[PDB]
Length: 111
Image 1 (cartoon, rainbow, N blue to C red):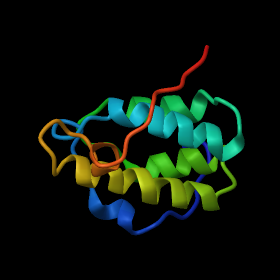
Image 2: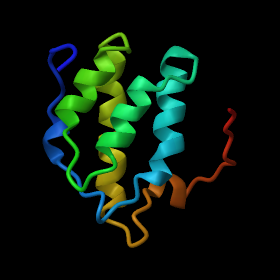
Image 3: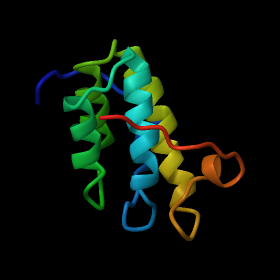
């Protein structure tokens, strides 16, 4: 643990990457984390990516790790937006959240 702190409750909704696609959240998370500060991180991204690379990520560690870079409040809001994103994704078939199903947008990404 890099930095201990408090998290949200919705983070206790658990998830299942084996059911939902995390890759579809890579740009969402990467964009979120990037937008959170304004620049493309890596340590925070890796944390989510590495964590989202499992079948059962620890939102606690996610928010805890995020808080290590974020302001702390953004971590709670971020997790309460991505954690739920998977919740809906895990409810899909392709493991995609309605955020992408309904809405739609290009995929921006740079080095």
